[PDB]
Image 1 (tube, rainbow, N blue to C red):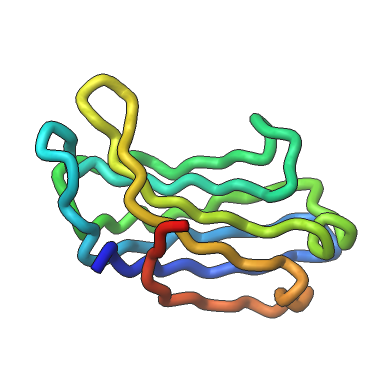
Image 2 (image 1 turned 45 degrees about the horizontal axis):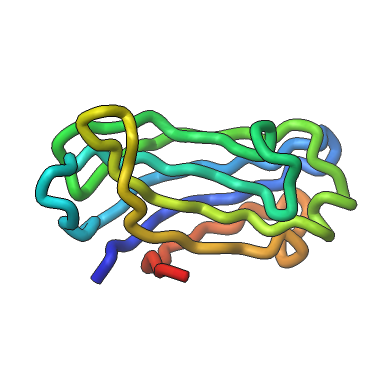
Length: 128
């Protein structure tokens, strides 16, 4: 009962561009009483060199059913990266002082993506 995440991936191979559309989440679990329902998504390429491997959506306010409707683009993604790397997608709530609480995540091996073929996802978040 952590919550369900919706997203779409496309690897525009010829332009070395992996386009990650973070669509929405539904039923994000209420947690820290002192925290806020200010959800946002973080992307990580694993293994990665930190900083540059990370992308982040807009933070919404007062919602457990956020609609981000946003495409995060990893430019300079190669066949070697698609072979090696895993896309970790993590949902978190931003708190009163710009810190956060981790709600849940999902992971997808980029080997399974096919060049120029959009894959849509509707998954439930998990904790590892």
